[PDB]
Length: 99
Length: 99
Ligand SMILES: CC(C)CN(C[C@@H](O)[C@H](Cc1ccccc1)NC(=O)O[C@H]1CO[C@H]2OCC[C@H]21)S(=O)(=O)c1ccc(N)cc1
Ligand SMILES: [Cl-]
Ligand SMILES: [Cl-]
Ligand SMILES: [Cl-]
Ligand code: NA
Image (cartoon, rainbow over all chains, first blue to last red; front, side, top):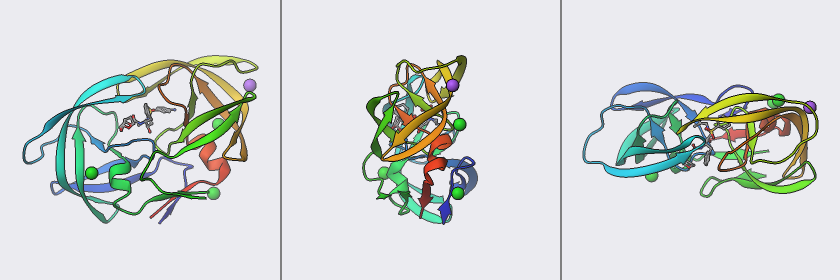
């Protein structure tokens, strides 16, 4: 797919059998999703965005489908205002920016 | 170009006569630049992201040169940790996300 940017680049993701909406975000290093349950252990992480730092739960090697493409990697869970797919998983689905 | 996402997609921009580095950010609705002076009128705005909100100055009809391509639109100025080129200007340079 070729996604233009006149609207937010929102896609359907599937994580834990659940469909969610997420933003494809080239300005995010990491993928951050709103509070949900994920399996296994987590490790702490602080991430810094526009407004300041937040604490998140880091889950590694999580299976996630993004716009129909399978990825397996790190998912951060915390109080983000929107689910964002960051570069760690955009690279796994082969995404590039083009102009 | 085609920009891969293994690393942050940073580019050189020219704005208000100044060269700056900025992140090409599909997750940003609007372009946000670190504190600088710009000509003309402005109005206050609050914009929110992970960590919460910051107060910015909204300037309209600002020209920016992005990676050699000129674009005009709104630029927000304030205490952002990173300069970001958001969708409002990415569209004008014909940027797309492809996978
Ligand atoms: C959270 C998104 C919905 C919105 N953001 C754009 C986003 O790309 C930011 C842009 C960004 C980048 C660095 C620092 C602050 C903000 N990235 C970000 O917060 O990423 C976090 C998750 O991975 C990490 O890597 C980068 C920081 C972490 S935002 O910077 O808060 C923002 C909000 C509104 C406008 N107009 C412009 C930008
Ligand atoms: Cl990962
Ligand atoms: Cl604009
Ligand atoms: Cl177009
Ligand atoms: Na103006």
